[PDB]
Image (spheres, coloured by chain):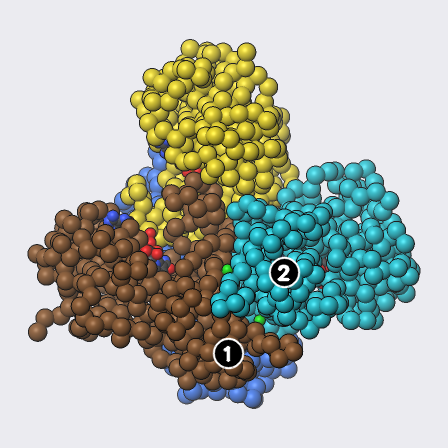
Chain colours: A cyan, B blue, C yellow, D brown
Amino acid sequence: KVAINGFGRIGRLALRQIEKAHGIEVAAVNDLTPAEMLLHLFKYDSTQGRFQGTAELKDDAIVVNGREIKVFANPNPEELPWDVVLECTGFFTNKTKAEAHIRAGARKVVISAPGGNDVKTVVYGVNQDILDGSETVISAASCTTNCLAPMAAVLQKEFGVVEGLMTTIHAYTGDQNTLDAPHRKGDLRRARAAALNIVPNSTGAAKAIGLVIPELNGKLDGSAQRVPVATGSLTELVSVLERPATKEEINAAMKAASSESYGYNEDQIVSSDVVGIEYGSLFDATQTRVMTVGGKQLVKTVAWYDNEMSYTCQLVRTLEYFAGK
Amino acid sequence: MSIKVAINGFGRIGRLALRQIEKAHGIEVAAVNDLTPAEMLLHLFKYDSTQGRFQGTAELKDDAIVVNGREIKVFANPNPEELPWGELGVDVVLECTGFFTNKTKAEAHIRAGARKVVISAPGGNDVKTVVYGVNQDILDGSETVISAASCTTNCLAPMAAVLQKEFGVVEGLMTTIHAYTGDQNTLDAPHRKGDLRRARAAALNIVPNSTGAAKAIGLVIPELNGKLDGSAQRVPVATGSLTELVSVLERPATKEEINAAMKAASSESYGYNEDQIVSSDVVGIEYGSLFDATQTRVMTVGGKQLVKTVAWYDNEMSYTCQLVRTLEYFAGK
Amino acid sequence: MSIKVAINGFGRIGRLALRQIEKAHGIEVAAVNDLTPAEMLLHLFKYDSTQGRFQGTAELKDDAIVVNGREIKVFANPNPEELPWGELGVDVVLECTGFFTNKTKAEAHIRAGARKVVISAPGGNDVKTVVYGVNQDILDGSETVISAASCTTNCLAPMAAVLQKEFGVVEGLMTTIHAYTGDQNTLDAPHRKGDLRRARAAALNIVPNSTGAAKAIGLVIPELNGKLDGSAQRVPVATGSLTELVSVLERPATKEEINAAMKAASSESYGYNEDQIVSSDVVGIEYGSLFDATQTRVMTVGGKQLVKTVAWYDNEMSYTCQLVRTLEYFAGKI
Amino acid sequence: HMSIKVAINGFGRIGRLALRQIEKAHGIEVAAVNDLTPAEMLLHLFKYDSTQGRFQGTAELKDDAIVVNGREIKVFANPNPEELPWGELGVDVVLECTGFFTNKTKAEAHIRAGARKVVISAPGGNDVKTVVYGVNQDILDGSETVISAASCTTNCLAPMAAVLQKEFGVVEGLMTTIHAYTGDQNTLDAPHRKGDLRRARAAALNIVPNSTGAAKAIGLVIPELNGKLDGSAQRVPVATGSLTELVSVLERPATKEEINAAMKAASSESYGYNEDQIVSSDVVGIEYGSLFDATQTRVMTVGGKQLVKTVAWYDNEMSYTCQLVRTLEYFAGK
Ligand SMILES: NC(=O)c1ccc[n+]([C@@H]2O[C@H](COP(=O)([O-])OP(=O)(O)OC[C@H]3O[C@@H](n4cnc5c(N)ncnc54)[C@H](O)[C@@H]3O)[C@@H](O)[C@H]2O)c1
Ligand SMILES: NC(=O)c1ccc[n+]([C@@H]2O[C@H](COP(=O)([O-])OP(=O)(O)OC[C@H]3O[C@@H](n4cnc5c(N)ncnc54)[C@H](O)[C@@H]3O)[C@@H](O)[C@H]2O)c1
Ligand SMILES: NC(=O)c1ccc[n+]([C@@H]2O[C@H](COP(=O)([O-])OP(=O)(O)OC[C@H]3O[C@@H](n4cnc5c(N)ncnc54)[C@H](O)[C@@H]3O)[C@@H](O)[C@H]2O)c1
Ligand SMILES: NC(=O)c1ccc[n+]([C@@H]2O[C@H](COP(=O)([O-])OP(=O)(O)OC[C@H]3O[C@@H](n4cnc5c(N)ncnc54)[C@H](O)[C@@H]3O)[C@@H](O)[C@H]2O)c1
Ligand SMILES: [Cl-]
Ligand SMILES: [Cl-]
Ligand SMILES: [Cl-]
Ligand SMILES: [Cl-]
C-alpha cells in the first residue's frame, strides 16, 4: 500500500509502473493541483506516450483500471491524512523535511531524490542489501546515480578505480526555463531556454557515490551538459584504473553483471531508443575506449538511461524490496 | 531632458524594450523592476538565446545595471505601489510583467509617482488599445493608462485594415501559428491557470490555444466590430510567428489587387515581403507585422470568393518595436 | 494462399507498413527493396525515433531480414523493372520511395511481374485515388495502379465528406499544420527539387509549403471537385499533424450539429476526440483522421456563417494504417 | 597590385559563411562560387540563414551570377572541378567546401583547372598539411599547393591542448565533443549514404554518438602530442554551436587557477577566454576558433593523482569559418 507525494513526472510514471505491481498499490496521491489536471497529465504524456489503461475522475478520486485512488491538493505534508510515501515533490529532499510525512500519519518513506548523508541511499541492484527494514526514511538517489553506480561498481570490483571524472549528457528537465527568464534558484544557466541550448550545470552524483559504493568514496567527480532532448540521457565516466584493462574485458565484465536493473547494449542506439526502458542503467559496449600511452591507460565507459522511466523503475524496485521487511 | 521610462517586468518584452529604447533619441530607461537580483537580470540582458548578444556594454553595480555607461536603477519590489517612480521623476512606465494588465492595477504606477502607463498586453476595454500605425490618433493626451494590444493584434490589425478599406470584410476567421512562450511548460506538468494544453511540453507539441486577438480588432478598427474571430496553434519555435486570416470580402478581389494594396500601405510598422521566407528570417525584425504576398490566395467558386492573407511577426521584437513607437507617441502627446 | 506484398522504399511509410502488415491475416510481406544493405534496414526497422522499438523479433540473415521468425528477402535494385516480382509471385507492390509517384513510373512494377501497385502518395490526376472509409468502393479489382493519396487527404476527406453530405459546401480553404518530413533539409542547404522553403532547416522553422490535398479532393469526393484549396505550414515536430478547414456551407449550422455529425460518422478510419489533446498524443494512432470537436467554430455575422473544423493525424501511422486498409481491400478483389 | 581572387567550391554552410567573412576582408575577394544549384537558390540561402541571421549587406541576382555589395560574383553549377574556369578567371585559391574532395588527388582538380592553391575546409588526408591557425601555420613553407584547415573540433581543441602541453605536459587525454548536428545527419530516421547507423537517425531528436579523428589530429597539429589523445562525439539537437571537453592526465601538478591563468595568457583573435555562465547559443556567430570556458575547469586530486577536465566552446560554423579565412589569408600571402 503506497502513496505518492508530488504527481509530477516521477510520481505519475511511478503509478504507471506500480499498476503492474503485486502486493503494493497506489492508494492516494497529493499535489498542488486539481484532480482534473492531474488526471489529464496521467492519461496523456508527451514523452512516455498514452497511458495503457483506463483512467477517469470520480468524486475526490481517480479510477485507474476500475480501482479508486484518492487525490489531495495540499502544499503542507504534515496536514496529509495518511504504509510508504513516495516523496516526489523535489521540495523535501532531506530527513527533517521528509520527517513531516511521518508526522502526517504514514510509516516509512522513500525519497525520490538524494536524501542527504544521514539517510541510507540505495541504488537497486548495487546495494539494496544494506537495508534491514527498520529504516523510516530512505533515498533512492538521483537518476544519474542509478545510471552511474552499476557501471562504476563493476569498474571498482574488477579493476579498481584510482579516480574518475563523469560527464552526463542529460535531457532537459522542468527545472530549466522554457525561454530565457529569471530562474527561481538563481542558476544563470538553467535560466536559459531549455530546448535551444547545451547548458552546463553541476551535479553531485559522482561525488556522492560513496553512499552507494563506499570503496569509491572520494574517487569520482563530474558535471552535466543539458541538451535539447525531452527525455533520455547518458553518463560518460573517464577513469584511471588500478590494473590494466582492455575494451573487451571491460565489456565482458559489464555483461556479466547485467540484470533487470543493469542492461547491456551492443547496438548502435541513440537516445530516443532509450525512452521508456525499464533498466536503471544500460551499458553501451560500443562506446568503451581504453587508451594506452607508454603503458599508461585512460578509460572511457558509457551507460544510457531514461532519466524518467529508468529512474522510476529503480524507484519501484527499491520500493518493493523495502516493503518486504 | 529625455522622457524617463521605467520598465516593470524585465522579461522577454521588458529586456528587448530596453534594447530598443537605448537606440532611440529623446527617451531613456531610468529604472527597471523585477523579482530578481541585479546579477540575474544583467546576465539575461547581455545574453539572449533568440535575439543575440546585447550589442553594447552592460556591467553590474550595487543595485543597478550600467548600460552603455548609464546607470539604471534595479528594484525587486513585487508591489508596484512602493516603487520610487516619483522620487526618480519617471514619466512613463512600460508595464511588462503580465500581472498588472488592467486599469486599476496599472494605476499603482501613477500612485507611485509616474505620469503615464503603457500596458504591454491587452489591458481591458476601459483602457484604449493602440496598434501603432493603425489607430494611435485616438489618443487625446488626457489618458494615463493605455494598452499596446497583443503581439497578434499588432500583426493582424494592419492587414485587416487594408482589407476593410479596400474591399470591405463580411467576416473572417484567424489562425495564428505561434511560437511557444513562457506561459507554456518546459515538460508536461501542472499549469498555474488550469490550461490543459499549455500544461504540455512546449517544444514537443502543436498546442491549440485560444486568443482574443481577432475579436479585439473590433476595438482597434471599429468597423470590424463583431466581424472577426480565431484561435492559435502554438508550435516548437522559440520565437517567430505568423497570422492567417480567411475572410469573406464584400467586393471581388484578386491576389494581385490584395498584394498591391498591402504594399501601398507599407510603412515602418507594416512591412511588405515577396520572398520565400520562413519563420527564423523574421526573428528580430522591427516591423510590427510583415505581410507575405507569396501566401495570398483568392479562391473563386461559382462567383463566391474566399480569401486567405498571411502576415509574419516576431511576437517578441515586432511587438517590442510597436510598444516603443506607441510609447514615444504617447509620451509626446 | 496468402496475399504476397513487396515494399519498394523501406522508409518511414515503408517500414511502418511492414509493422502493420505483420499484424494482418491473409497478407504478408515477401520482400522489400531499397538502395541499402540489409543491416541498415534491419537497424531502422528495429529502432524508430518517433514510433518506438519494434514490438517483435527482427534478426539479420544473408541479404534478408527475419521478422517474427519469417524470412523477408531484401533487394537493393534502384530500377524497379529489374526486380524479380513475377518470379516470387508478388501480388501487390507498396510503392513508398517517393520516386515513382505516377502511373508511368509505377508501372515498372507491373513490367517486373507484380500484379498490382498501390502508390503511397498522390499519383497524379489519372489514377484512382482512395481514402479508405470514404471511397474504396470505386475499386473493382481490375485496376493495376492506384493511389492511396497523401497523409493530408486522408485527414481532410472524412471531415469534408460529412460537411458535404450534411450541409453542402460552397467552398473552403484548408491549412495543414504539419510535422516536418524527409523532403526538408536538416540545415539550410540547396534543395534537390528547387524549393526555397524546404531548403531550410526543418526543426528550426515554420515553413510554408504547397499541398494539393484540398485541390485534388475531387478524385476522392466527387461532389467537392473544384470547391477546396489550401496550403501547408511545416513546423518543428517530428511527426503528428492537424488539418484546419475554413468553409462556407450551403445551409446554417451549429458547432453541436457539426460535432454530432462527425461522431455519427466515426469508424476505425475516422476517430472522434473530445479531450484537450496536443500533437504528441496523436503519434502512433491508427485512425486515418481524428476529428477534434473542441476546435469546431461556427461564426455568425449578420446571418452569414463561416465554419472551422479541425482534425488530427499522425502523418506517419495514420496514413500507414489507411494504406494497409486500402491494400487489404484492393487485394481482396485483385 | 591585384587583390587575391578566391573561388568557393561548395556554397554550403561553410562556403556561404566564408563569403560573408571574405566580404569583410581587405586584400582578398571572392571571384566565383560553384555548387550543384541554380543561382537563385544560392542567392536565397546567402541572404537568409536560419542560425547565422540575414546577410548584412546587399545581394541581388543576375544572369548566372550574384551581386554582393555591388560587385559581381560568377556562379557555376558544374559538379566536376576539372571543368571550372579557374584559370580563365585568374583564381588564386579555391576554398574546397563540398565535403566531396577531401584528399589531395581529388582536390588537385582545381589546380588543373587553373587555380594556384587549394584549401580544404576539412581534414584532407595525411599527405596534405593540416593547419590550425594560431597553433601551427608556420609549418607551411609556401611550396604547398593543397592544404587543410582541419575540422571544427581540431580548431577548438588545439589551442587549449597547446597551453596544457607547454605549461604542464600532457601524459594522455580523452576528448568528448558535444556537437551540434550537421548536414551529414538525416532529418528523420532513414538510410544513410555512408552506412553510419547513428547518423541515419533523426538529427533534432537524438543524442547521437559518433566518431571523430579530431583528437588524433592534434598529434599532427601539435607534434609533441603525437599518439597522446583520442576521443569521440555526441551530436545533440542544437543546429549550431558546440563544445569540446578534454579529460587529461598532466605531467606536473596543476590548479584550476593556474590552468585558467595560462589559458587567458594565450588568448588571441583565434583563442578566446570566457568567464561568464554562457550556454551554446551565446556562441553562435563568434569569430574565435575556440572560446575557453574557465567556469568549467576541474582539477580532481585523489591521493596525489590528478585528473583534469578543460572545456572550450566553438561555433562549428562561424568559428571554423573564421579559422578557415585566417589560414587562407596566411596561405595566400606566401
Ligand atoms: N525529472 C527527472 O528526470 C528526475 C530524475 C531523477 C530524480 N528526479 C527528482 O524527482 C523529484 C521530482 O522531480 P520531477 O521530475 O517529478 O519534477 P516535476 O516538476 O514534474 O514534479 C513536481 C510535481 O509535484 C508538484 N509539487 C511541487 N511542490 C509540491 C508540494 N509541496 N506538495 C505537493 N506537490 C508538489 C508539482 O506541481 C509537480 O506536479 C525531484 O527531487 C527531482 O530531482 C527527477
Ligand atoms: N513574449 C511575447 O511574445 C509577447 C508578445 C506580446 C506581448 N507579450 C506580453 O508581455 C508581457 C510580458 O511577457 P513576456 O513574454 O516578456 O513574459 P516573461 O515571463 O518573459 O517576463 C515577465 C517578467 O515579469 C517579472 N515579474 C512577474 N511578476 C512581477 C511582479 N509582480 N513585479 C515585478 N516583476 C514581476 C518576471 O520575473 C519576468 O521576468 C505579458 O503580458 C505578455 O502577454 C508577450
Ligand atoms: N512521411 C510521411 O509523413 C508521409 C505520409 C504520407 C505519404 N508519404 C509519401 O510516401 C513516400 C515515402 O515517404 P517517406 O517519408 O517514407 O520517405 P523516406 O525518405 O523516409 O523513405 C524513402 C525510402 O525509399 C528509398 N528509395 C529512394 N529511391 C529509391 C529507389 N529508386 N528504389 C528503391 N528505394 C528507393 C530511400 O532510400 C528511403 O529508404 C513519398 O511519396 C511520401 O510523399 C509520406
Ligand atoms: N558544418 C560544420 O560545422 C563544419 C565545420 C568544419 C568543417 N566542415 C566541413 O566543410 C565541408 C562542407 O560542410 P557543410 O556543413 O558546409 O556541408 P553542406 O552540405 O552544407 O555544404 C556542401 C555543399 O557542397 C555542394 N556540393 C556537393 N557536391 C558538390 C560537387 N560535386 N560540386 C559542387 N558542389 C557540390 C552541396 O550542394 C552543398 O551546398 C565538409 O567537408 C564538412 O565536414 C563542416
Ligand atoms: Cl567536471
Ligand atoms: Cl476558431
Ligand atoms: Cl491557401
Ligand atoms: Cl572515446
At 80% across and 57% down in the image, what residue appears? Answer: A128
Q: Are marks 1 and 2 in contact (CB under 8 Å)?
A: no
Please identify, in this view, whether the residue under mark 1 or under mark 2 is nearer the observer. Answer: 1
- Say which of D137 and D42 sits in front: D137
Ligand 1 under 8 Å from disc 2 Cβ: yes
Ligand 4, what quadrant?
bottom left
Residue C181's image quarter? top left
SS at mark 2 in the image: loop
Label 1 lies in what chain?
D
Q: Which mark is residue A174?
A: 2
At 36% across and 36% down in the image, what residue appears? Answer: B299
Q: CA distance from mark 1 to mark 2?
A: 42 Å
At 25% across and 63% down in the image, what residue appears? Answer: D147
Q: Position of residue B265 (x, y in %)?
A: 31, 57
Q: What residue would you read off at disc 1?
A: D251
In the picture, measured across the screen, residue D63 lies left or right of residue A195, that is left
In the picture, measured across the screen, residue B3 lies left or right of residue A107, that is left
Amino acid of disc 2: Gly
Neighbour class for label 2 at 10 Å: few (<14), some, many (≥20)? some
Label 2 lies in what chain?
A
